[PDB]
Amino acid sequence: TFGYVHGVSGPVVTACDMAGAAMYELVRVGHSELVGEIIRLEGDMATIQVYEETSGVSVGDPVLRTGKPLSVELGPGIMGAIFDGIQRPLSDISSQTQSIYIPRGVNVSALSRDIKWEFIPSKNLRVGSHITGGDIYGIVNENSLIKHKIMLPPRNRGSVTYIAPPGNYDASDVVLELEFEGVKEKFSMVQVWPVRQVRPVTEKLPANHPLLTGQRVLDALFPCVQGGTTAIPGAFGCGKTVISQSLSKYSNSDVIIYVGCGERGNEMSEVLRDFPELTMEVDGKVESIMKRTALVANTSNMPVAAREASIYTGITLSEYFRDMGYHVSMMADSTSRWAEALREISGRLAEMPADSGYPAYLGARLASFYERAGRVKCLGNPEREGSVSIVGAVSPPGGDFSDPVTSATLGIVQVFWGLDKKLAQRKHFPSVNWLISYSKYMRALDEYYDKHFTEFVPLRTKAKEILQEEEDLAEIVQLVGKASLAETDKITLEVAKLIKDDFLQQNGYTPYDRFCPFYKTVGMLSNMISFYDMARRAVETTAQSDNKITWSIIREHMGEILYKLSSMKFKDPVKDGEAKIKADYAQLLEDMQNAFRSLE
Amino acid sequence: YLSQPRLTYKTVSGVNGPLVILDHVKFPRYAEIVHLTLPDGTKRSGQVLEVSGSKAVVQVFEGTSGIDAKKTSCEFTGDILRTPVSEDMLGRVFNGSGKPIDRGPVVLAEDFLDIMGQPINPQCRIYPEEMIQTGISAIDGMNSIARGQKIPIFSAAGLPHNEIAAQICRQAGLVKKSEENFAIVFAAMGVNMETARFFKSDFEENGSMDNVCLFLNLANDPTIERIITPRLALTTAEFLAYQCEKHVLVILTDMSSYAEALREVSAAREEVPGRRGFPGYMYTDLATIYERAGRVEGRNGSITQIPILTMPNDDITHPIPDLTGYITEGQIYVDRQLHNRQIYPPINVLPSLSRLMKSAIGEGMTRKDHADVSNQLYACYAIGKDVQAMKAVVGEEALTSDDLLYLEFLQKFEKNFITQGPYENRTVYETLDIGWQLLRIFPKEMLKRIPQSTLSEFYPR
Amino acid sequence: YLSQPRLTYKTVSGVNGPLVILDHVKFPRYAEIVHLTLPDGTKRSGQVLEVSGSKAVVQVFEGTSGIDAKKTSCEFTGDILRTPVSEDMLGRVFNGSGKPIDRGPVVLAEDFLDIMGQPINPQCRIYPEEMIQTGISAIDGMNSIARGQKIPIFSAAGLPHNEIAAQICRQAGLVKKSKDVVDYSEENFAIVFAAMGVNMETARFFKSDFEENGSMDNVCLFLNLANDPTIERIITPRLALTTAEFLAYQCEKHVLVILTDMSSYAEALREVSAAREEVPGRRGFPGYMYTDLATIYERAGRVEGRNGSITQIPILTMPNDDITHPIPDLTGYITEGQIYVDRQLHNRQIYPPINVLPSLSRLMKSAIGEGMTRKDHADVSNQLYACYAIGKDVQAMKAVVGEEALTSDDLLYLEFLQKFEKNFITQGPYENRTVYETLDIGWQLLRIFPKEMLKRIPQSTLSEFYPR
């Protein structure tokens, strides 16, 4: 434990002269107790890699031996706080120090250690009853919304020797204890779990439910799936955290875990403003997003290893809240920043540059990251079910999809959505290209969409072929001159224009467009497709025989009904009842029938 | 046989990346398998690589993490990696290393075999002649495959090569028509959960689970096991081919991930690189994998092999596809342009290649003029692409008549020959009839490659 | 605090290149400052690079030459580098090492601080809330600078970026005078300027110009000529940033730090790395250049509860005018926004040659607004940009379409182009334009057309401003 504090070629610094101790474990160095990482072993000499600065550290400095490797604390009160890459509660640190800068070696637990919490035991098992790991043995109400379930970790079983009564207990208190065959062990409300490994589950299950998004665009065309994996481009001026806001408010998820690398205090303060601004009437009462979500972020000037550990601690937290029977969504944004972080790590390992300095095992880490996702039946007596989604924000260099990370990730995710500066510069909102976006989950969601609604699948298919066909005929209408062509093609492009202008765009500030219920999306799309079908029937019938019905005839004989089409969005479903809107849609359909009948 | 007891050790001179170095070892043997007991009681394994003096080096398979010098124990066995093989393994599931996944018991073995196998003697090699019916016209008709071949399939990220592979498995057989079948061994090299579910369900569907041995290594498993899994599966195939006289088909998937894992393990030792940083000897290693296939004199079984690999960034000069193109004797080159047009099965033919066709076909095999149809169809396809590239600039006015004929041929051939469907399985003679139907479009005085005789006896109808 | 006597060694186990290896040192520590005394009596400073048991290594700042084995003293300090910060440093001029050079006295230190600085808590960041004026009409009107934004200025070898920097220095300030000059008199603004990797002519020019402008009472100046030791190149920025920090957060002021020629910083850092025997990274530059530039740039912004701010305007040159060179690439990634200068515009004898077409900004939307400025800013900027882009592409069209087929409105677009490049961009080295003058000239240039063509301006402001 003697700090043979060698001289260095970076913030890394090593030591030696210590007994046998396993690697990938973190040790504290010097009297200020800077954290570091064991890498190499050689006899009684172990290389270490510190995170913070290496200034001033002297040889012979004490090297605090540790008993655990890098691990996150887990327990109640996580939601609403803010953490760095090594799990430090920055709000509590700022309160404690009354200082502006981060101090060195702030050795304070992440969660509270003096605030008691109400606790409801199982009330069905006694002292001595056999229990195994993963089983829920207590509940606690963190706040008005969510109750932090409590369960045993894996790799623990035995005959209970103490059951706490219901009441109020602090973190350090022993709420549980159990005698294994030979020994016993005490458990508190706080569990420490290694970062670089995956919790067990009963079994992984297929994805069979669609993710709820506030906007009908990208929710009816390129549907993301609960428990899915996707990627979204991200650049200034178009919107990246706009998706964060939309998912955080209008989604069926039970928690949001946001991960940040190289971000400003803007996004933190703005989502803090979203906490009392973007509030939901879940129980008929506006309620802050702070009670649900959690944030873990860092800045560029923090140590590199912290930047790397950020994404893993984020994954771990997402898994931990998933284990409690919920529906997590994790926005692992700034993925290219994590790529640069990995390049940085490899810069001080004498590794062979696979491509542009990227270490060899970049692909392995990419796969191991995106793998930890999907629906699972959880391991434990309650038999609950949940899932995790991931949203990796790809940030290419100016629109070049050539970096190994970009291509490697685009062949792993299944949903990818467009974002182009041109559409945002066109005043077209939301900026979704629709020609570089796709979704490979369509075979999976067919079952769900068939059971519940039974028409939506034909509607989306027909929409897709019509859109691609319009993009094809753009060239021919360029050739001719956009003033002469067949009537059937005219009506086709006109329905394309109608869907583009009234359905594939959504005002984020209009009260009735602040959220778009899916039944309304279905009704809108179905009524539109019916209008186009009727117009096609009439125009073709009169084109083949005589009295050809031109687009002028349809504009003047149905123009007020076209105003009705474009005004179908003026519904305000938040107050107006669903039956009222359904009746309006059906009545408009009957009016459409009357107009087409009198058209011929 | 060997009654010598197995020594255990406590010497760990030091760790450095994925390696573990031992000292004071009494007579180490190169490439001998070793078990490791960590402080927590969980278990691992490894294989010796470099030996010098009393020092030795050990590659850990499960990834090195949590190794303490004073508390770990390194047991030695004293022989090369050796695996159990048995006929009844068919109808089971295993992970990368060979341990069961399907809630079953370990394989009571009919014999122990060398993981690396050993080279077959070229003199006693019966050259493959018998033809396989795939059904897909892009193979039967353009790049036919005889049993014993080792042709790969080239794809790209986000392309439906999995569907093609599954269909190939479903409809394999013999063109010349007791009921023969296949015994298929399948190994996965870092596929995602979705792929595993798809393949497992597909094999469940057609009732073929009774005759498929599975080897599954998702991305969760430590990368080093990906080096061993292929050779293990291939050894099982060789056993079933020459000790049970069965006919076997092998499907290794995503060997690109295998190449990545090879790069990862090589970087630890600091070997000399090659193009794009891969090891120089990576060529010989891929040769050690691929070649083990074909038919041998005095037997009845045979090994066919269909590896699958993705092409990073569609760059064909990339070392992995190039060295595959050197070792194996063909390629398929799944296209993405057709996939963008929503066509099934989207397979390019212009760069596909099949070296065994020169003896696969002929009189008494398929039809008299099978080669001629192939040559002429390819030539028309090539000139059609050239004419399209020419039309992209000159304009419709500059087109002569034969350009129009070539362009309509291109369109018709693409919508007819290539497009088959998820389960349509054409007979070979149907495919030749269709090919002649496409050839008849041109007047007889332009089909240069076909001989005059075949044109006289077949073209007018 | 420290009370022990210092040590000194006469041990030299060897020398090599810019380093000096010794041994038998008691309990050495990394980053410890070391003095040296040669046989001929010269004094030189240095720093500790490597430490291993009783072996030590010291990189001599002033450059190694004529260091004997047996006749060489080497005193140790036992502390890392510490800056003597002080408010009174304004009006002074220093060298890279911090020794004054203007015939003045050693700084009577008011407080000692760590040169490296400390990371600022992201929790205590405050978003910018108001703009500033740099004195350049082209920059303020078209591309706002908030309080705490980090806007670089890409240039190339052979352009007059230094003159632009001097102009920005002698005219930077605030525009709180919107309401009244009486409340504007409360001025708490200062500038710290770090000339680094600069040749002699430009150093003298800077000193003379700064002294001529008469506002040296609020300017700190740091000079590092290209003669001085290469290591002092990568110590000048740290001193400048520590001073800016101490002024910003201990005097509640509004400081504006301007860094020059970051390419020379990169080159000096490269040389330090190569001397330190480390393995090269991409393009020969070290791998952790990203982290280093991050720890330099990230020291700015605003702090909650402190009335003060730090704004950064680094400058750098692009080798071969290559936009994908690593230095500008990383600088763009870390920072927010970018401003260009274009060879052609300088080659049109237009000063300052500021090419607004590829110039962007990141906080312009929130830097400006009602109150802190007029209500007629953002629309004016959009209209000027749209008009100018139309005019330029339209000149490209008339180049081949012929001037005879042009409409009269086309001549109006050309008139807008020529007048915009004649008056708005061209200002002259001393024409101190304010923001309000800039918007006045903008409206005057917009007056050429009717409001009907001006389709980016809302009708509500058209009824007010257009008929002037």
Image (cartoon, coloured by chain):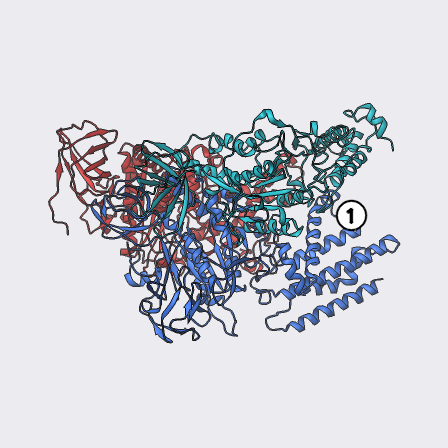
Chain colours: A blue, B cyan, C red
For the residue marked with disc 1, what is the amino acid? Ser
Tell me the quadrant of the picture where the C terminus of chain A can be found.
bottom right
Quarter of image, res A100:
bottom left
- Determine the residue located farthest toward the left in the rendered image: C5
Q: Is residue A282 visible?
A: yes
* B316 lies above or below C312: above
Q: Is residue B6 left or right of residue C229?
A: right
Q: Is residue C428 visible?
A: no
Quarter of image, res C169:
top left
Q: Considering depth in this image, is B444 or A299 the residue closer to the camera?
A: B444
* A592 lies above or below C231: below
Q: Position of residue C405 (x, y in %)?
A: 67, 38
Q: Is residue A540 left or right of residue B96?
A: right
Residue beneath the point at 74% across and 70% down: A587
The 10 Å Cα crowd at callout 1, few under 14, some 14 to 19, many 20 or more, is: few
Q: Considering depth in this image, is A312 or C180 the residue closer to the camera?
A: A312
Q: Which residue is mark 1?
A: A484
Q: Position of residue B208 (x, y in %)?
A: 65, 48
Q: Is residue B84 left or right of residue A594?
A: left
Q: Position of residue B455 (x, y in %)?
A: 83, 27
Return the chain for callout 1.
A
- Determine the residue located farthest toward the right in the rendered image: A545
Q: Position of residue A69 (x, y in %)?
A: 34, 52
* A447 lies above or below B18: below
Q: Is residue B189 left or right of residue B335?
A: left
